[PDB]
Amino acid sequence: MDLYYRPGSAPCRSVLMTAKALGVEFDKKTIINTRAREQFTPEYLKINPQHTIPTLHDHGFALWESRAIMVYLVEKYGKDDKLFPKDVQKQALINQRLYFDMGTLYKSFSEYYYPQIFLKKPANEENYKKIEVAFEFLNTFLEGQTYSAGGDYSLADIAFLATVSTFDVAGFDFKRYANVARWYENAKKLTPGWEENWAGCQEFRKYFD
Amino acid sequence: MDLYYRPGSAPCRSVLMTAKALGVEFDKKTIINTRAREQFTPEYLKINPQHTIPTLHDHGFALWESRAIMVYLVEKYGKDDKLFPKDVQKQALINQRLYFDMGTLYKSFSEYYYPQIFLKKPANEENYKKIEVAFEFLNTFLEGQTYSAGGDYSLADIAFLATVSTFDVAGFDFKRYANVARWYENAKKLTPGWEENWAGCQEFRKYFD
Image (cartoon, rainbow over all chains, first blue to last red):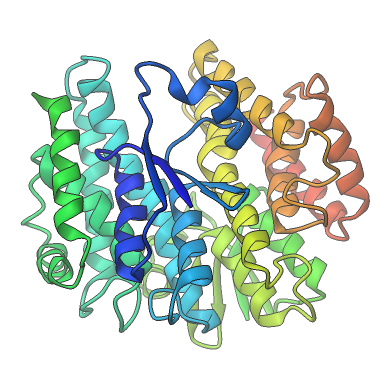
């Protein structure tokens, strides 16, 4: 299978960490140059009409949305179901956390930082407060818990590592969210794709230079 | 099980349509008065610390995020898997569509209309264009297709009916998206919860009065 991605991209990095966790290798990894509008070519649009990254192309099956890709890889190529268990309630909790990551936590990242790093606008304090709101919720989810979506390390932890590491490299102070700080340092140790993720975070950091 | 909801709410309506499709009845349906901050009570926060609607409470299991609830109901209470099939690739496509609904299509709704109906600001033309972008993608997804996520009616169709019916009641002209218009009228006919959904849309319409 081929992965169309950018190493700096948090959703891309979540997919890469998932593949590493599963012992899955991509037959091909294609870096999309979005400055050159490579996502807008007829060939790319044929695979992904929404022209987003990451895009997975697996024996003729095209898939996008990082969190859909993550679940797909576990369900198809996973030697076991630990990251996304068969149990309906356990999957449901992971799914809720994945939606939270997309719609609340990473949303708070893009809404605060993108206008700065891409649009060159000053920091918006109300958008900063929305990050704090999001971290407060994550902190509450982690109250009394080692992992973010149940008693075992799961896809939720990988998605959150991709997002939180982006906050980390951006210089956001999340130390004060005590449960988040605890969870983060421990989860890093349990993530075989961590080094690759942090290296990719450095590509993203270039936007802040 | 108990559902905490508001009839006007699109994510709530997606859950209600799913339950009807499955022949599932809620043992209790509790309308949350958000003007009275009922979602902020210790009792509500105990079930859902994020204080959102819809929230499902099923024999001690609390779940939120409408699309997580939808999948949960199919997987747990579904007599068959038709709406969310066992097949990994079919589930993956539905999942991508569900993320699109949350992050792109319904996002375009809230970003355009919420500042108007709740914050009393004038319509923002750039936000209007983002709706058109979203409908264009949905229109492309439906090119040559009867349903929105594969050859059979699925959870993707229910999520999109909840969202698109909200656009409909809001007065957005989507007729020009020919595939969307076709899909919508046909999908309504195949949705046993449709009448309840459209009635709930009238509660939402009150915000436009």
